[PDB]
Length: 145
Length: 144
Image (cartoon, rainbow over all chains, first blue to last red; front, side, top):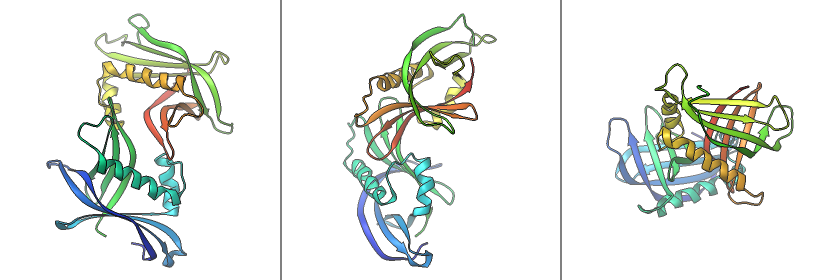
């Protein structure tokens, strides 16, 4: 992807995720999330947000999202995001924490979901209330690093 | 839609943020009517009808009809967990939250009607510190 210089890791923690895939059992497992911000020198110092999902018991379980400042403009509209690119990672971190802290008896309840598909996977954090699954964020990840 | 087998569940004004093209966002009271009934041609076919109108503009008119079969795709796309019979009740609950909303609320519930080419998309969103959480999104056609 982007060669990040001055890259800074903002978040590096395990998160409980409901991993869904067609034809397979749903598995609830801890996945490692790393959120990095950086400047792409090969691309006129564009700011990049990188999120990497990995498993410490499967070296081939690898999912990566990269969002540049330019990618964010479309993301912001599609997802109804109201803050700027700089403030976006903090909001994601807050959502991940709600998933980490979620208890089985919660109402409403937050959960992280990763649906694995062909050459792509969709990560979402949803708030489940009495009558629907309310999506707080939906993000597309590509396989690998 | 059969105007005889129909039952009106809700018929009152609601504050709505109307977004149109080439005009400034307007906050105005629009009248919402929610009806349940059956199709004229097929009595076994249950339908939900929503009508939006203005008490000041005789021509501001938007109508939605959702059949029970249409609900299945709607249900999947929007992650709705209740059945067709229970759906209108949830919409009414959301409208009520929009009615009771105060400008300083956090989060704030608001109803939004976006008009495009004269056709529209209605939604109720919950607005927090960083995004609009869509509780429902519905497409309306001009007229009655």
